[PDB]
Image (spheres, rainbow, N blue to C red):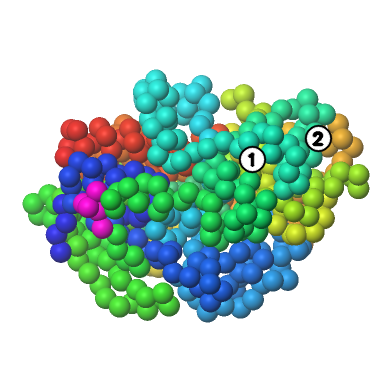
Amino acid sequence: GYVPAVVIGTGYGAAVSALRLGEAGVQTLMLEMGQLWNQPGPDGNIFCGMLNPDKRSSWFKNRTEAPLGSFLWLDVVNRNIDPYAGVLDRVNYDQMSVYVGRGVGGGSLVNGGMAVEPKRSYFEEILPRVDSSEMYDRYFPRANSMLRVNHIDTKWFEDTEWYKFARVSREQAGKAGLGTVFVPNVYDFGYMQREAAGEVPKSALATEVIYGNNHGKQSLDKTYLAAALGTGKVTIQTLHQVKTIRQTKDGGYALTVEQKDTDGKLLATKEISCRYLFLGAGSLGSTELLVRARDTGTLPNLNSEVGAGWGPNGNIMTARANHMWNPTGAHQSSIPALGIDAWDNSDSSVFAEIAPMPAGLETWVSLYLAITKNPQRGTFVYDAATDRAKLNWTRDQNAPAVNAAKALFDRINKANGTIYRYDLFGTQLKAFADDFCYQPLGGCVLGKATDDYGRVAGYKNLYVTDGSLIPGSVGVNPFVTITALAERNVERIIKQDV
Ligand SMILES: Cc1cc2nc3c(=O)[nH]c(=O)nc-3n(C[C@H](O)[C@H](O)[C@H](O)COP(=O)(O)OP(=O)(O)OC[C@H]3O[C@@H](n4cnc5c(N)ncnc54)[C@H](O)[C@@H]3O)c2cc1C
């Protein structure tokens, strides 16, 4: 069971790694716990929509759940389901629920495709040891090209009924002296125009996104992973979850892997050894594997930084009630295109995404998912009893995030004479959802738990390439930063180490 290189996971950091390793001629094996999403379901489609969720929508749950913010309208379509290897996983900790994708392509399968580059001045603040010039001149441009990032046609956007909810919020924000910015995406906008014209099968215009897109979205299986497979040096094994990592007596690495079926049944436990080990299991997946290894003594040389510095990228979701004369439209595109930029690097910094409402009818609701600058951080601690890493994060740690978001939208409300919706997130009457996370960052911070290139401190030929490297915050949607950073690290690693 020997393979020169093994990449754990198939997300952004893992995808970049596999391609570059394949191109360099290194035989690589990717292990992914989720499924390869290429089989059509009971309805003929691969993925289920948000209006017709089934077992494909969730990772081993006994009932579907309405997307955050749409409970009042989408709870009606929920049904009981058999636990299955679905695409979206809600991982619940004490006071924090983290949503992560499961399958070949990782989070790219379930995300809104927003590809944004962080402000340079902020990037320099969060990672002072990294050369920002190399990132902005070479790696970010390289990431955007390979991801197939594209821009929306501003004329179509301005006249289509599908983005009226976006234009409405732009008018409101404008009144409060705030500005909006167009956000690039990996969803083919040209394809989106043809959807509106009824020329091609709808996906983004058919209330699809969080459980995957049947068309239009260029997820990693279509970009990095397709190219990696094309090298003839990369293979991908699905439904294979890595449990433990240890170092052989001669310096190599050995892994214990559980092969399961789609129903969760354990089919076999395998031992796979390698020379170069790349971790791309995400902020949660990589961190857990490392804290388990350290605290169970299989990798006793990991430092105390492993598991620290976790942040939810300041994620806060709020909602505003529009006046009757400001309808947002019954037909709303599932892919965001506009954002409110109020990020200046201060404590009141806010970058808000104008999120769509999948209801299908007029709600007069304007939904936002704010990204704030909150210094609070959590820590992953290993629980030897249950054999799981537990996140030590308390709801009160999100107060700064809530305050910053509230400061912004309080301005918009005052200028437009509007109020917040308090009944969208639960019966608790909360205008701000502060216990969820779509963008987990940290746990194995760059330069802390690793060197400046993701080499895990204390070991040789052991690398971390994903979201766990980011120090809890970036100020914008994270996947481009994760991809560009992986480009920077793997290139250096292949040159010096491999
Ligand atoms: C609803 C939603 C909306 C979002 N929208 C956006 C957006 O618009 N723009 C943006 O920039 N970002 C967005 N994100 C966040 C983005 O998806 C994540 O930041 C990104 O996917 C993180 O990349 P990663 O490489 O670190 O790990 P991930 O993409 O999470 O991938 C890790 C992979 O490793 C696998 N893995 C885990 N542990 C194991 C194990 N032990 N063995 C085997 N395999 C394992 C996982 O199953 C998974 O496939 C959103 C995410 C969600 C949930």
Please determine whether, in this image, residue 382 is positioned above or below residue 128: below
Q: At numbered mark 1, what does the secondary structure look like: helix, strand or loop?
A: loop
Q: Is residue 115 above or below residue 7?
A: above
The magenta segment: 231-235
Horizontally, residue 225 falls left or right of residue 125, namely: left
Q: Is residue 283 visible?
A: no
Left or right position of 249 against 402: left
Residue 105: image quadrant is bottom left
- Are there few (<14), some (14-19), or many (20+) residues within 10 Å of tag 2? some
Q: In the image, what residue type sits under mark 1?
A: Ala
Q: Nearer the viewer, residue 98 or 111?
A: 111
Residue 200 can be seen, yes or no: yes
Q: Position of residue 194 (x, y in %)?
A: 62, 49
- The main secondary structure of the magenta stretch is loop
Nearer the observer: mark 2 or 1; the answer is: 1
Q: Which mark is residue 255?
A: none
Tell which of 52 and 85 is nearer to you: 52
Residue topped by disc 1: 337
Query: Is 334 in front, or is 177?
Result: 334
**How far apart, in angstroms, are the residues tagged by discs 2 and 1?**
16 Å
Image check: 474 left or right of 385? right
The residue indicated by pointer 2 is: 172
- Label 1: few (<14), some or many (≥20) within 10 Å? many
The location of residue 177, given as percent across then percent down, is 78, 25
Residue 130: name its quadrant. Answer: top left
2 or 1: tag closer to the N-terminus: 2
Look at the image and say whether residue 10 sits in the magenta stretch: no
Q: Pinpoint residue 119: horizontal percent, then vertical percent.
A: 53, 26
